[PDB]
Amino acid sequence: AGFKPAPPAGQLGAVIVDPYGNAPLTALVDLDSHVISDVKVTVHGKGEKGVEISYPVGQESLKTYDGVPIFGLYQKFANKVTVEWKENGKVMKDDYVVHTSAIVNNYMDNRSISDLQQTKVIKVAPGFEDRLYLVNTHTFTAQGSDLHWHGEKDKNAGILDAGPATGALPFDIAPFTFIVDTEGEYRWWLDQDTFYDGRDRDINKRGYLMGIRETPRGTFTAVQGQHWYEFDMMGQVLEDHKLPRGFADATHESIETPNGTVLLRVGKSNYRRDDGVHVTTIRDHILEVDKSGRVVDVWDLTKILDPKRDALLGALDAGAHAGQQAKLEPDTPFGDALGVGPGRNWAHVNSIAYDAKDDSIILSSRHQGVVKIGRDKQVKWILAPSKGWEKPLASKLLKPVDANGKPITCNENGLCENSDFDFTYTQNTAWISSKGTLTIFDNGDGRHLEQPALPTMKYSRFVEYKIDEKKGTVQQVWEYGKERGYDFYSPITSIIEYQADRNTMFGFGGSIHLFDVGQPTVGKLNEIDYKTKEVKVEIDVLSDKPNQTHYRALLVRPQQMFK
Amino acid sequence: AGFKPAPPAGQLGAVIVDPYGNAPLTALVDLDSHVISDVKVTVHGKGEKGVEISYPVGQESLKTYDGVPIFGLYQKFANKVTVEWKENGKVMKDDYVVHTSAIVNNYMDNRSISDLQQTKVIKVAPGFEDRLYLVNTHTFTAQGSDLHWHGEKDKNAGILDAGPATGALPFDIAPFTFIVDTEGEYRWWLDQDTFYDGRDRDINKRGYLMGIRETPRGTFTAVQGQHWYEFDMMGQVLEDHKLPRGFADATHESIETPNGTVLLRVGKSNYRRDDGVHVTTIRDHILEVDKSGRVVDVWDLTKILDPKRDALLGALDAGAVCVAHAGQQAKLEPDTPFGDALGVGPGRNWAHVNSIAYDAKDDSIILSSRHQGVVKIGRDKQVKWILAPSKGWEKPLASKLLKPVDANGKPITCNENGLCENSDFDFTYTQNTAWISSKGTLTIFDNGDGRHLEQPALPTMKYSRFVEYKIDEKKGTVQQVWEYGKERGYDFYSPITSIIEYQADRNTMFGFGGSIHLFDVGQPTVGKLNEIDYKTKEVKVEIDVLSDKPNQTHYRALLVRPQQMFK
């Protein structure tokens, strides 16, 4: 006779490239029954300003991988790797040359600018040369949306009519997943085949890879369509769960709790409306699942909030026919569409945050605002312009004040007077910062509940708030980006997150220049000094097809990847 | 256009037979967006003496399933079911007629007695009519073992010779998993295609389905070949993990701990022997994994115990090899080729661990080695005690041997073979399921092969026990405090597998002998379910399960409680 395995490369076992087969820019040093400890890996930079990646590897990883994880390689390159360990009270070291293969995009057509998305470095301050960023973007499939959930036909339906559609099964795209360093180089790639398969019609392998978030084990959870996952930086798929049978279309987010549970955002399949019509609802539906995939709890937002509030809804750019303000029709067929009511995109929830302090969740509804909902499924507060909100939900809205806690005078549209307090509009990632505060990407479409005279007048903000839940007072304590204009405006997607290690504000604008037809879409990575607003890091990712938005990115840390 | 879904059956949604596709005698009442709170299901017994099954349903389950779970139906029958619930403050109730289809055995050939295994009720005391028992058994495939792991050629082998095998891949069979009531009726069935596919050569669908154990949630874990699992009684596969890449051939046990981890009994792939031969080791490694499938810890038994000890290994019947030479004593050979074969050293079946117990009190594990005895190993990988005949053990292990005492705690005299004098005390031999009981004692199934470390005069001179010991870890003393099956002879004798477990609820001893009359050629093998009153040793239950092909061992059975199946 047969063929032998690979022989050892040094003082341990063989060194295998891409062990699990889903991460081509990784490799594994096989243990070959050696008892080692105090392990460290160093991947050396390419060229003269090449960025070095170095990390410890803990005891759970060795056992799990039966070897030393090699993360941080370059593609099609003779990587130089050094691994240090201890064996029998003695210090050890090997230097390996690890050749890699190429990175492939399996989804190209005449729309392709080229096979990979282009990076452009712009600002790398001192003491940020080590930073790594995981980019969660995507790339159009050749035939685009090809499949649709089947729904229930209505009274007003033509007699001969074929049945309708429901839900959001067409929300389907190829993933483009990678890590980029401060030299604009790819240092990681999750094979597109790992979760997705666009040419085949296995709905198990279809959807929109989203909500990539870190776990307390240095791993990551993600969603795609009708499944949710866990995976590590070696490309090992740790969990693969179908959604519970009453639920569908999980998009936008997934986060592990401190209690071992996992928060998902989904829709309800076969949802019975009060008029007896069945629909798959749209992004208005939060699960708490466990590691068995079972449901621990569910928030039905159609019964917590107000699916009839069209305040912000009525005021939206229909290009996300661009620019045009949203003109609602009350005969809008059920499905993934702007409209009121269950079976229509009335909420568009895109972010979840758990609050251990009071066992509550915090949510950002693109089309309504931001809320904290209790375990008791009681709304505890709301952050939105006061228009549209009926009683008793109106009782829950927060009151903006100043540094001295005196009320800020605002109108029902969010326009405040004599201060810089503003709310958020079509916002994202309303999360809780390590500082104990709420951080939000304010995409800013339909700001102040209107379209502006000219598109280019829109802008996006990073914004931080301080909430006295007990008083119902909210305070805007930090903002950045208003004064950067249409080149800093992301209509959709996007993220910010407070980094306490370097006191920065991390962000990613995912759809910059989305409307510039024929032009690649810009994903802009930023670390902003929290104290000075100085740009410490600015890196741009360009879509590989024109007008192809990015979703999110994360600031990842190798010291944590391998528990 | 399109065909409509199923319309409501009663005052809720439609009623779905076998929703997940894995348990054909189950059903689901779809929830159709109704909000309900105090659910109860009752499945009425078939015929005049049929057993009724009734259980509450928790919220999580209603949520997890989006419906009410219906467990306990009869095959090919118009099952009469009653669901009771609260909706909008007021008491509700529906009666459904749930037709079911047939149970299929997909693995039959000329050895087949009939398609399904036969049951024979023997004894059912009053107050024990409700009992249900999950039978973990199996049935031969038409091809038998067809797959080997590939090994590393070693110096002794020829020059033109192809490489050898290693590991325990041929340890492969089709499952036969059903629940039984005190009328010997089939009330649950896990589709064979759920985990296993014996006509196809996808190894992820191969192995020997075992170590079926309840979880703190009412669900069950299980191992088969190179995967481990979690499932529930609706046939829903909750987890499906590959073994971590260092490991292979998982069998016998899988048990969730109070800490969310799961303990597995495994072997090691590509193990580097001192002489630098790479083998896959056989049933001598313990994994602790998480729900992410990652290794939390690992016990290498080739370095915690003694793979050279052949005190029991040589005293054995070559009848319980793997699959003529029964009755005959084991003769160890030095040149025994690595693989699933009796012998010493890493790469050979020197240990055959087959039970794991987690001791929460001190973060230790308890193992049953068929071929060595019963030990407690710490989190620190340090051997804490041993229950075995003192023969063959060197220092430092010898110092760990427990010392037999009486009720007043005074030494008992037992020779080096385990033979004691002037007491009923006896050690356990090729035992199974060494678990901790609710009382905090050690219960064991003393299969009893190679008893007192020899083969007896005549083959029939063999017997199994149920046995319970009390250990004073602080002093190293072990005390036998209960036993049963001694007097019942060869007809109560299970050479392999099998299981016991104390039940505080009715003060009984649960047991299952998986291989009674295993060696009776041409005869079905008997799996005997038993409950034994703890106080009186009266037989409260006794039910026999007969293999569907001749000489086809069973593995284990569980005492399941439907009150606990849907959290």
Image: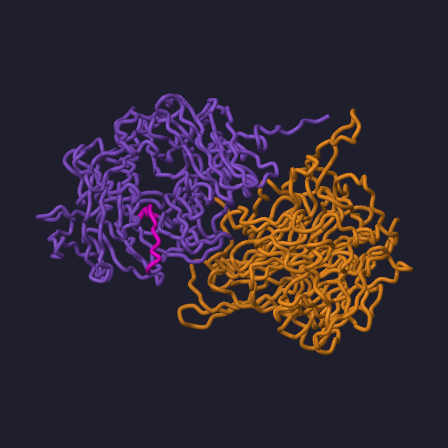
Chain colours: A purple, B orange
Q: Position of residue B371 (x, y in %)?
A: 75, 53
| Left or right, residue A532 beside residue A221 | left
- In the image, residue A31 lies in the stretch drawn in magenta: no
In front here: A391 or B369? B369
| Left or right, residue B415 beside residue B87 | right
> Which quarter of the rendered picture does the N terminus of chain A lie within?
top right
| Left or right, residue A498 beside residue A108 | left
In front here: A230 or A452? A230
Q: How many marks?
A: 0
B556 relative to A200, above or below: below
- In the image, residue A351 lies in the stretch drawn in magenta: yes
Instruction: Tell me which corner region of the image, top left, top right, bottom left or bottom right, holds residue B539.
Output: bottom right
A554 relative to A431, above or below: above
Residue sitting at x 69%, y 63%:
B180
Farthest-out residue, right: B457
Q: Position of residue A426 (x, y in %)?
A: 26, 44
In front here: A5 or A256? A5
Instruction: Tell me which corner region of the image, top left, top right, bottom left or bottom right, holds residue B419.
Output: bottom right
Q: Position of residue B360 (x, y in %)?
A: 56, 62
Q: Is residue B90 visible?
A: yes
Q: Which residues are magenta?
A: A344-357
Residue sitting at x 16%, y 54%:
A400
In front here: A470 or A193? A470
Q: Position of residue A512 (x, y in %)?
A: 26, 32
A519 relative to B496, above or below: above
Q: Is residue B224 visible?
A: no
Residue sitting at x 47%, y 25%:
A79
